[PDB]
Amino acid sequence: GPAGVSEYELPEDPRWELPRDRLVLGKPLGEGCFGQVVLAEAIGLDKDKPNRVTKVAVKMLKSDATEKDLSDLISEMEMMKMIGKHKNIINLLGACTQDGPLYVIVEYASKGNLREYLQARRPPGLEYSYNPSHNPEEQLSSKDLVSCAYQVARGMEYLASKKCIHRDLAARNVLVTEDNVMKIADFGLARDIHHIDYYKKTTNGRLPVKWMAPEALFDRIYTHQSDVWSFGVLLWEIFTLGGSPYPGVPVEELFKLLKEGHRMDKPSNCTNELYMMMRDCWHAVPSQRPTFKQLVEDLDRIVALTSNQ
Ligand SMILES: *CCC(=O)Nc1ccc2c(-c3cccc4ncc(-c5cnn(CCN6CCOCC6)c5)nc34)cn(C)c2c1
């Protein structure tokens, strides 16, 4: 019977389609752009091991979704296919387009987003703000922190090689897996064709204008060079263990300040070398910023020289 049949033509790709009875839905992972994200166990996700279970994240479409929401979730999924797999991005694993509501299945990152992961690992004392976690975890070593940055840079280098511009690279858009692998999220989202509201917070209270390069702020120009600017902000987030950028600065003053040369001060626990890397990412002139290729090479060297003691 036609009950529950989509009015739309959802694209069935036999390489990726999973019968939804292979998903055992589990705990909520929060509200995404298009609907709930839910942890699930997938049976037989790898057709070579039909009797094994893999934990996955299931992106669903909310019941009151618009046609644009549906189109946007399909577009993200097809973009992930074209971009292909990398260790440091959230990868596509499958989809359910038949016999029920649309699900897009991606890799599960059990430790959640990087900002709250780092906040929960703040040690006491003078160099960081307080630890807000009631389940605090062991502090990371200096090498772990640089390694976090290296992994994100490696993921962005891959995405840039595939001509993918992220446009909102921030610690809240990096997720951390059970094995502490950093994975960039939301890289496949299509760009809004409408102008954005600079003063509208995200559902988690963030103001994305604080990650925008000046040419994105002023003229809405987004390039790989503006993603490098954002990476500089993400570096500052890492070495403040989840800090909020531009403390005390009202957002409507930000472009004026950046234009006059204002940049964030160095975090208390941050080498001169990594601060110089942040500042280079924040070159006013887009052509003068490093590339992700260069950032990867430099972070590789710095990781190797940085103590894990
Ligand atoms: C429109 C913008 C938007 O909503 N983006 C968005 C992107 C990704 C999202 C996830 C998500 C996706 C893929 C994998 C994944 N794995 C895990 C989690 C996750 C969420 N919360 N946790 C638990 C974190 N705690 C931390 C403390 O200790 C216990 C674990 C894991 N999320 C994803 C989910 N949402 C809502 C996304 C939105």
Image (cartoon, grey):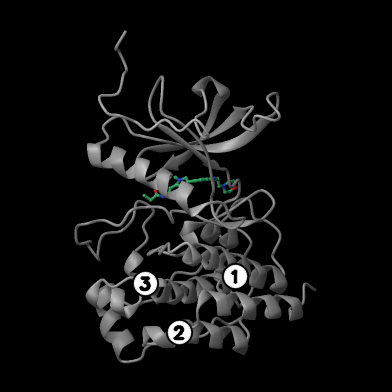
- Give, as a three-letter code, the residue at label 3: Thr
Q: Amino acid at mark 1?
A: Ala
Is 294 in front, or is 140? Answer: 294
Q: Is residue 44 above or below residue 203?
A: above
In which quadrant will I find the C terminus?
bottom right
Residue for badge 1: 149
The residue that disc 2 covers is 289
Q: Residue at x 60, y 74 (%)?
A: 296
Splitting the image into 4 quarters, where does residue 201 fall?
Answer: bottom left
Q: Are marks 3 and 1 in contact (CB under 8 Å)?
A: no
Residue 253 lies in quadrant: bottom left
In space, the residues marked 2 and 3 are separated at their CA atoms by 12 Å
Q: Residues within 10 Å of mark 3 (few under 14, many from 20)?
A: some
**Residue placed furthest toward the left:** 194
- Which residue lies at the image location 54% right of the left edge and 84% below the top edge? 277
| Circle number at residue 192 | none
In the rendered image, the vertical position of residue 230 relative to residue 26, given as above or below: below
Q: Quadrant of residue 42?
A: top right
Pick the residue in front: 241 or 281: 281
Give the number of the disc on residue 223.
Answer: 3
Toward the top, the furthest residue is: 1
Circles 1, 2 touching at the beta carbon (< 8 Å)? no
Q: Secondary structure at mark 2?
A: loop
Give whichever of discs 2 and 3 has the lower sequence position: 3
Left or right of residue 86, residue 83 in this image: left
Instruction: Tell me what residue is drawn at x 60 percent, y 89 percent.
Output: 272
